[PDB]
Image 1 (cartoon, rainbow, N blue to C red):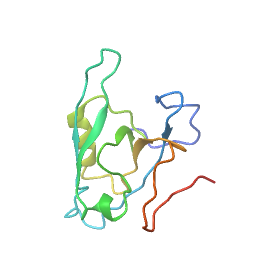
Image 2: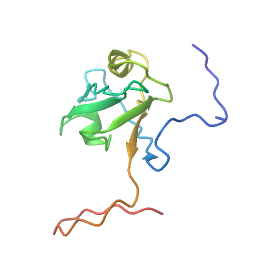
Image 3: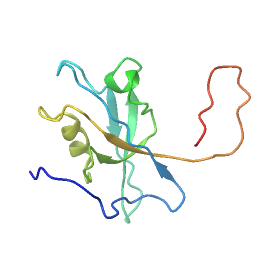
Length: 124
């Protein structure tokens, strides 16, 4: 490996409109599992893309990792994944404590809420 990262001269491959969100996690005990399954989609020769297949409500992420089901992972801790297994393998590293996974989240989004419940994230 190479321990030394101070300044990233651009490094992201997302849609020319979509947005990302760096979510950091913690594993106070290896016994803790991300609780976030991944799956493939392909259907594209340009580039597949790892996405969240399942997300446990009671998991490191669930607890913190706002991540959810249907989240397109871009990088893991700042790494560029290129395989499903890896996407998981990385999440299954007996070294990385702070798991900072990336996900593609839309901004603004159409207006279709109307739901009596504490919920409604806004930009700053």
